Length: 166
Image 1: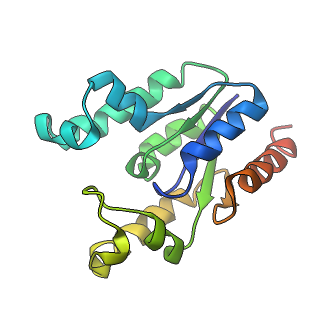
Image 2: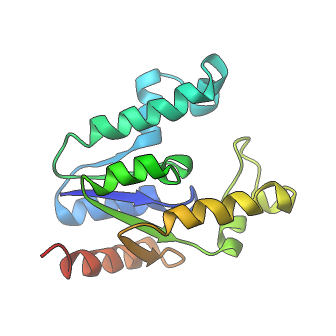
């Protein structure tokens, strides 16, 4: 079984993913972390040395490679999860799970590429992107409330997975 976690960077994908993989006895992997370890460069460092196109294509490649495993929980980056092609690929391999957080939570927890708190960046700079990426995230097989503590979100996912895929 392949389980994909999608949503904004500050939605707890990585943490919930680990807890989830532990309760299902399957390995956990985070695309961005794998992309960096493979290139030996930080994400920022990546679109610098190499263009972003090279990064956007790299993370998709990494996603596919990770998806060779039949049992695994894979957390995705903000953009990758908002990539419909990558999202459709994910559905053809397993269950996609959108850990949804409201705009106010996003604003207080997330940061931009320069690690600056979004709560201090101009609003118009990120409101449209949040609204648009969320429209793609919503296309997920399963959607759970990510405002809750990580352990509670895991129970939500498990309960959803249980009544599922019969």
